[PDB]
Length: 141
Ligand SMILES: O=C(O)C(F)(F)OC(F)(F)C(F)(F)OC(F)(F)C(F)(F)OC(F)(F)C(F)(F)C(F)(F)C(F)(F)F
Image 1 (tube, rainbow, N blue to C red):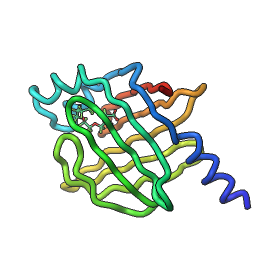
Image 2: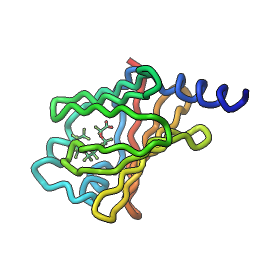
Image 3: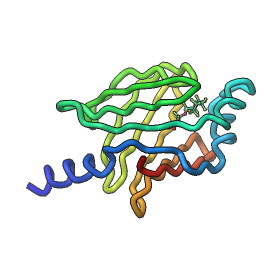
């Protein structure tokens, strides 16, 4: 009933081609993660395209850039293995929390999370590691 209407309407809102339009404190966020000088210099100029789609029962997230191209495929709320763009081998869970799509990565006893939300048609991504928070805005292409 309302459960399937919530899950279908939420996933539908996020499924699009998203272009990065704005970044805030992403450099600090990469520094808190332990991303070195070399990669950070690339990461601060790289303009990603994020494609979110439904491929069967799975939700797919493709991050396309001149640095590295990543692709993750998952069932909502079911843990999966993920090798990140900065070569961290995580145990990750992508889930729904109200109007938010929450991505939690765990590796080496550490934890980082990315919260994606739709705000006035834009996708706002909040990246958190400890006290360090970054905000990235995306628009539909
Ligand atoms: O979603 C996006 O648009 C995202 F590409 F920027 O990825 C991300 F969501 F920000 C991340 F959280 F995945 O980033 C990261 F965690 F992988 C990272 F911070 F390590 O990123 C990184 F360092 F690898 C990087 F070099 F900056 C990078 F070039 F891959 C990029 F694309 F993220 F900027």
